[PDB]
Amino acid sequence: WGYDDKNGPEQWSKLYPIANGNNQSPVDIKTSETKHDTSLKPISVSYNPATAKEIINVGHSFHVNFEDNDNRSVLKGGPFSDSYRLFQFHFHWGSTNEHGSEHTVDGVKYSAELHVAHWNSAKYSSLAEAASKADGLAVIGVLMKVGEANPKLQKVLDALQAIKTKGKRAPFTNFDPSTLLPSSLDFWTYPGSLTHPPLYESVTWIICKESISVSSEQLAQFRSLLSNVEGDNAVPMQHNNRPTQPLKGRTVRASF
Ligand SMILES: CC1(C)O[C@@H]2[C@@H](CO[C@@]3(COS(N)(=O)=O)OC(C)(C)O[C@@H]23)O1
Ligand SMILES: [Zn+2]
Image (tube, rainbow, N blue to C red; front, side, top):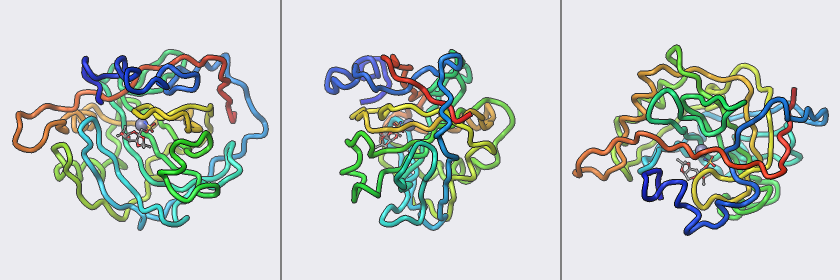
């Protein structure tokens, strides 16, 4: 699977029927229709830089994995009663600065989007087990607006030269991804899914209202990553964001 014309988002329903489900992500957040929930507690993240493990080129994107054998790096608060264990973060981008984010706010598309994923370690004992549970995954989404260079992305960006082609991987250690989050953690939350196959509707989304910046050149670096295996003709990763999906009755709650 990928985002090309033949194997993109529009063709995912073929092997994954859940793609047309009632809890799919991403979605367009309409602020006039969100419901402020007074019960929503503040988002609390506490990550240990030592849990950073490695970075991998998966063909359609790349992601940074974290050791998730214990609760050294966790997420709490918000709409959760359980503690969620950090295990990965990655980005989504588009072919041009005009688009790239997965979620949209009042129809506005941003240039990219950061996803920090965690799994429910209070109820399950592994990502594999939690991945398909309705309450198994928690993912923070941060909209990235094209503008000033984001120094926080530096380490991530510098590591890409070692995993240029599909399947390459390299250690990525000593990094706390909470340093990538916006100053304010006011958020929107709704029940959704993974935005890439298998598309399980096991994700409780936490979308930050505040965006973070990224320069046009930094985005270029993402797009310069290759989706081909070493040796083949270079084929740049131009985009990997899935179109917004129907809310189908779901209510998007706001912590503010
Ligand atoms: C690079 C990218 C998109 O992110 C990886 C992998 C497969 O899908 C994901 C999607 O997670 S998401 N986009 O719902 O946060 O689901 C998991 C299993 C959480 O890993 C994510 O590809
Ligand atoms: Zn994602």
